Image 1 (spheres, rainbow over the protein chains, first blue to last red):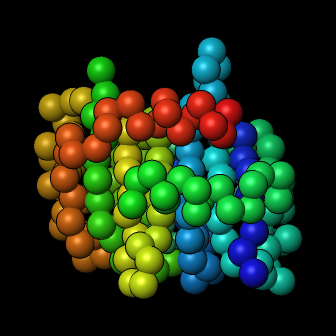
Image 2: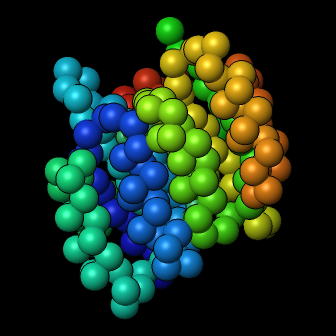
Length: 90
Length: 90
Ligand SMILES: CC(C)[C@H](N)C(=O)O
Ligand SMILES: CC(C)[C@H](N)C(=O)O
């Protein structure tokens, strides 16, 4: 159903616009997002919750090509992490 | 120091690109992001952690104008919410 993408990116302006822009240009909806800075660095962590799609693998390719994306992978996180976060903020 | 912006937006493709694009186009960095869909609706809640700035007023003005942004407000969330989230996901 859904899948979680984990990105390590540079914490500088415009990075999230590039990443989400790849989905926007494909009418691909992003269901959940978490972005947290990494202490003592110039980078941030991004979690993207998206519907599992045949187009996903070619998109991971496009994300990795972005200069400000250091790494992009799948399903390393708690698959229900956004449900647990929502319990405390919704 | 920093402030948290709360947005209610439609859960449609491209919406996060529009919101962050406003910051990107002004070289305004977004430090933390949380996006959660709202149960039983076509809307999502976005929390944006950004440096408190006089530029924010105009920025908030532009965010509210976006058709897909239903509402946008300041200082209604726990200012340290992204520190608390990091305790459990970093
Ligand atoms: C990491 C990301 C959210 C970046 N800080 C940006 O403003 O686009
Ligand atoms: C709410 C937001 C993340 C929207 N679903 C988007 O894909 O841009």
